[PDB]
Image (cartoon, rainbow, N blue to C red):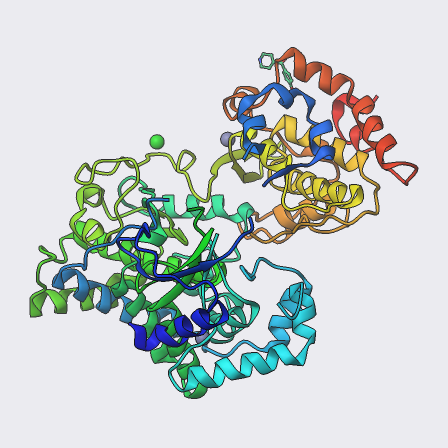
Length: 574
Ligand SMILES: COc1ccc(C(=O)C2CCNCC2)cc1
Ligand SMILES: [Cl-]
Ligand SMILES: [Zn+2]
Ligand SMILES: [Zn+2]
C-alpha cells in the first residue's frame, strides 16, 4: 500500500504544501483517497474541407450530432474462485511460452523512443519543456529518467503517476514503460503468424479474409460477445498472470519489467480533477491503467486466455470453477498441449474485441468461468446463452463487417464496411486547435485516400474521395495527429493494386488493374442498406454539380496546382 505508493504521494503533498487537505466529502468508495490540493484548468472541431464536399450530409443527424460535444471506474471486481484462478495461471503460463517460442524479449531504446516522438504518435503523455520532441533533445530529462530508472532497480517509484482526464503520464514514465514492455508491440508478439488468434499489424484489408478463414473450420456459430467496460473488469489476478511475461526475461530487463508491473500496474497513483477544482490523489491496485499500446497487447493476451478457458468449459474439459481436481489440471494441461494452437486459430482477437468459432454451440451457454473472471458480456442477461452468427459476412469485428465482392474478371475481394454515416461523421471531425487551412486540407486528403483504399466499394465514398483529392493541391502530403497505406503521395490506383492484388496472399492471379472502372461496387441495394444516399434527390444534385463544390474549396485554398480525379469515374468520363 503506502509503502509502494507513499514516496509518490509524499512527493506530491510537498509540491502543494500550501493547499493540502484531507477532504471528507470525497466521492470515492472503491478507490483509496489520500488528499486534495488547489488546481484550476480544463472539444472536437469540424474539418471544413470535408464538410464543404459532403453537403447532403449537413441534414443527416447521425452525421451532424457526432461533432457535438463514469460509474464504471468507481467499481470493484470480486476475486475469482480457486478453480478459476488455477485455470487462468495454467493457461497464462502456457500462452506466454507459446508466444515466446519464436520471439526474444528485449529492451526498447531511447533512440527508438526518440524516433517515435518525431514521427508523432499518441503516447498518452502530459514543466521545464513544452512539446514531447523538445524534451527528448534535452539531456536533463534523460537524467530525470536515470533517477527513476535506478529507483525502479531498488524496487521503488517516485514520479510514475497517472493523470485521469484515458490515463496520461509524464513522458519519462512512458519511456520507462516502453523500455520494459515496448517489445510486445515493436516485435509483433500479437501478429497472426506468432499468436494464431491475434491480428496486430494485419490491416483492415486483411481482417475480412481472416474472418473468412476462421469460417472455413468445422464448428458451430461464430460468437462475438463484447465485454462491458473491459479495462474496469481487469482483476489483480489478471495483472499477475500478465506479469508472468517477466519469467521469459533476464538481467536488467527482467528487473525493469518487474518494477513496471509491481510499481505502476499492480499499485497505481492517479491525479483526478473534481469541480467541487481540487486535484484528488487516489490509488487502487486493479483495473487497466497502462499506455494505450501496452494496454492493447495485455488486453489481447488476457482476452486470448479468457476465450480459451470459455472454449475449455464448452468442451467439458472441467466441470466446476470452485475447485480444480489434480486430474482436471492434468486434462487442462493436456488439452493445451494437444489442441491449444488449433483452438487459438479458431479466434480473431484485437484487444477487448473477439470472434470465436468454437468446436460446437455448447460454447453459447458456457458462462461460469467467463462471468467468474469478471468478463461480463455487454447487453445480455448474465446467464442467458450467447447469440451466435451463422454467416461470417454478418459478424461484427473492430467496428466493421465484411462483404464478399466479385470483380468483373472473377477475382474475389473481401472488403471492410461500416454504416456510411459513421465514416462521413468521423472524417468531418478534426482533433485539437491551431490548424492552418493547409493542415485541415491534408487531414481531409488522409480520409479521402483511406476511403479510396478501404471503402472504394461505397458509391458515395468513392465520389467524395475523388472530389476531396481534386479539391486539395495534388502535391500536398496527407497528415494525421491498422497498416496506413493511404498515408502517401503515391498515385492511389498504384497503392490499390499493391494492397488488393500484389501483396494479397488470398489473390492467386496477380494481373494488375489498369483503371478505377475495373474496381467494383457493392450491389445498389447493399450500398443503401449500409447507409448510401443513392436514389435521393439531394445526392443526385451533389453528384451532378460536384465540380462546383470542388471549385468552391479550390477558391478558398487559392492558386495552387490541382488534378481533376472525377473522370476516373464512368459518369464524369464525358
Ligand atoms: C451510381 O449508382 C447509382 C446511383 C443511383 C441509382 C438510383 O437512382 C437508385 C438505385 C436503387 N434503386 C432505385 C434507384 C442507381 C445507381
Ligand atoms: Cl447470421
Ligand atoms: Zn516510477
Ligand atoms: Zn456493409
